[PDB]
């Protein structure tokens, strides 16, 4: 260790300093357009709620990392903190994918979507996603999560190395079903959105290009945030499932910097889905 005394501390500090008011503003904007029959607003609201949950769970981890990886809050509390953090981290990606699929359906099939009480179906899908992610992260909750090591760290909810192929398969599945399934759906939906309006007589070149930047570049932001973490996770899980203590000692600060860069997608979501959107930043621009 050694870099977790400074870097993830400062990223978490920036997140708790800016994203929390930003996520509150995005939540208010999303709720404002839920009132107007919209069914993008429910996904945006749930995304902002998940981001707020992760942001408020961040600073126990801030202390954790800035005190040279030590846990003193209690064996019971790290279960809850890791559960909230690692569940919001995947729920965010799921709801980005849902927003992408919703936009693709609305644009490519305008005369057939959404139509029939759009708030109810979207709320049902949101609840189903929450249930599925909660079930996915329940097996980690069943845990001996607090770990004492010889080298004066005493982690919780993490282990170096992994344990007996089990957490390794769990991590491989977590990667391939909480990322690259939602990210893959999001990328395909945005590509289909940008290919569906190839033929529209009304959209000019100026307003085709901004849709192009959004469709190819919002998934890029999501990947650039959530990607290094899951790539490193899959790398460790595959190496343990093909290295000794040298490999993990080499990619350890990479792993705990990729986690911070992954939680950095709690500033981008409120920004890219409230301020970048002209509609939201007409209502959520100055609460006072």
Image: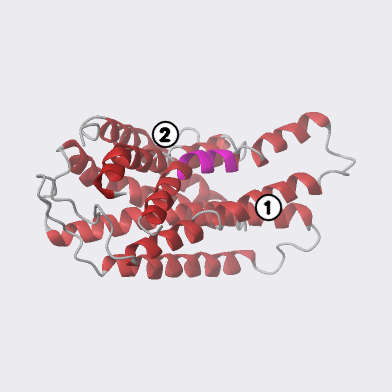
- Check the image and report above or below for 19 versus 166: above
Visible residue check, residue 49: no
Which residue lies under the disc numbered 1?
Answer: 189
Disc 2 and disc 1 in contact, CB within 8 angstroms: no
Is residue 224 magenta-colored?
Answer: yes
Label 2: element kind: loop
Image spot of residue 208 (x, y percent):
77, 35
Which residue lies under the disc numbered 2?
Answer: 288
Image spot of residue 150 (x, y percent):
9, 49
The picture quadrant where one finds residue 122 is bottom right
Is residue 13 magenta-colored?
Answer: no
The magenta-colored residue range is 219-226
Q: Earlier in the sequence, mark 2 or mark 1?
A: 1
Query: Relative to the observer, which residue lies in front, 156 or 12?
Result: 156
Quarter of the picture containing the N terminus is top left
Q: Residues within 10 Å of mark 2 (few under 14, many from 20)?
A: few
Image spot of residue 145 (x, y percent):
20, 61
**Horizontal side, residue 58 vs residue 88: left or right:** left
Q: Nearer the viewer, mark 2 or mark 1?
A: 1
């Amino acid at each position: 260790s050694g870099l977790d005394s400074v870097l993830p501390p400062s990223l978490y500090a920036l997140v708790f300093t800016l994203g929390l008011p930003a996520n509150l503003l995005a939540l208010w904007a999303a709720w404002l357009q839920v009132r107007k029959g919209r069914e993008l607003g429910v996904y945006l609201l749930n995304l902002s709620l998940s981001d707020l949950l992760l942001i408020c769970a961040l600073p126990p981890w801030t202390d954790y990392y800035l005190r040279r990886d030590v846990w003193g809050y209690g064996p019971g509390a790290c279960r809850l903190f890791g559960f909230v953090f690692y569940t919001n981290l995947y729920v965010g990606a799921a709801f980005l994918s849902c927003v992408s699929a919703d936009r693709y359906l609305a644009v490519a099939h305008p005369l057939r979507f959404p139509g029939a009480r759009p708030i109810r179906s979207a709320a049902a899908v949101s609840a189903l996603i929450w249930m599925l992610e909660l079930a996915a992260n329940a097996p980690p909750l069943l845990g001996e999560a607090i770990h004492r090591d010889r080298y004066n760290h005493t982690f919780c909810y993490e282990s170096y190395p992994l344990s007996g192929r089990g957490a390794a398969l769990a991590n491989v599945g977590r990667v391939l079903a909480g990322f690259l399934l939602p990210w893959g759906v999001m990328m395909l939906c945005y590509a289909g959105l940008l290919r569906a309006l190839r033929g529209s007589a009304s959209c000019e070149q100026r307003e085709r290009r901004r849709v192009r930047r959004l469709a190819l570049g919002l998934p890029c932001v999501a990947l650039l945030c959530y990607g290094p973490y899951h790539a490193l996770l899959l790398l460790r899980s595959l190496v343990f499932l093909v290295g000794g203590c040298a490999l993990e000692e080499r990619l350890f600060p990479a792993y705990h910097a990729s986690l911070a860069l992954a939680t950095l997608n709690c500033l981008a979501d409120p920004a890219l889905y409230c301020l970048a959107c002209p509609g939201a930043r007409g209502e959520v621009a100055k609460v006072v």
